[PDB]
Amino acid sequence: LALHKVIMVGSGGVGKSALTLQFMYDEFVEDYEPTKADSYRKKVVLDGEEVQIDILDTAGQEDYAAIRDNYFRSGEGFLCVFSITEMESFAATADFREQILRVKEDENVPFLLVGNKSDLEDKRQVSVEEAKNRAEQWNVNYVETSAKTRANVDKVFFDLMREIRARL
Ligand SMILES: Nc1nc2c(ncn2[C@@H]2O[C@H](COP(=O)(O)OP(=O)(O)O)[C@@H](O)[C@H]2O)c(=O)[nH]1
Ligand SMILES: *S(=O)(=O)c1ccc(S(=O)(=O)Nc2cccc(Cl)n2)cc1
Ligand SMILES: [Ca+2]
Ligand SMILES: [Cl-]
């Protein structure tokens, strides 16, 4: 089977684990240990082809730069998550983008900008416009998700796999 290696990146509390666990187990998990990194593997039927997705849910604990870079080098695609309710998490996406680009040396690395917590519109700190503008500057797609309601959860994982399939 094709193996699509996806890495979840983003600052703390944005919903990396909640997105991963909603995709894997169809549950909204609100208390997943913030410091725990884990990998998840699932067989999925992508546009009618059975593939395996491997998701690395990062938790920011790896501080040794060579090891972090080694992990990013192994990844084939990235979900770069921020929370629409935390502007600083959106600012932080620039750092993950640069880290990925330094390692992959390919501006067309499969990569989605993911604005999570779309069910908290009344707490929005990041405008759709500014996120779309950043995605346009980077030539990536912007998708808003909710790990709580499941909105666009399958979409971000499937669309990332579609970019891996097309580009690699
Ligand atoms: N309302 C809402 N809460 C969310 C969403 N995603 C995550 N959360 C909550 O935000 C907190 C942090 O989520 P988590 O997935 O652990 O963030 P991580 O540090 O990026 O892995 C938890 O309390 C989750 O319930 C979402 O889409 N909507
Ligand atoms: S490793 O398998 O020993 C490992 C994997 C992931 C982490 S982390 O997610 O806690 N930290 C982190 C930070 C930036 C990029 C990445 Cl891939 N991971 C630790 C150890
Ligand atoms: Ca987490
Ligand atoms: Cl791991």
Image (cartoon, helix red, strand yellow):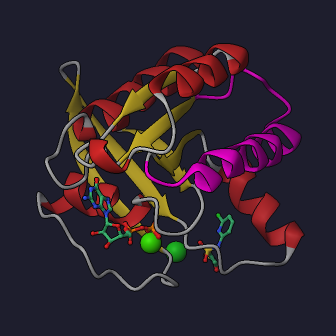
**Quick check: 83 left or right of 150?**
right
Seen in the picture, residue 109 relative to 95 is either above or below; the reply is above
Residue 144 magenta-drawn? no
Quarter of image, ligand 2 = bottom right
Can residue 94 be seen in the rendering of this structure?
A: yes
Question: Magenta residues, as a range?
Answer: 85-110
User: Residue 63's x, y, as percent?
Assistant: 79, 78
- Position of the C terminus, as image quadrant, is top right
* Percent coordinates x, y for residue 27 in the rendering: 12, 64
- Residue 168 seen from this side: no
Q: In the visual, does 9 lie left or right of 128? A: right
Q: Position of residue 113 (x, y in %)?
A: 53, 34
Determine whether 168 is above or below 146 in the image: above
Percent coordinates x, y for residue 36 in the rendering: 48, 83
Where is 109 relative to 52, above or below? above
The residue lying at 40 percent from left, 28 percent from top is 143
* Total numbered badges shown on the rendered structure: 0
- The residue shown at (52%, 20%) is 129
Q: Nearer the viewer, residue 100 or 39?
A: 100
Residue drawn at (55%, 69%), measured in percent from left and top? 12
**Which secondary structure type mostly characterizes the magenta part of the structure?**
helix
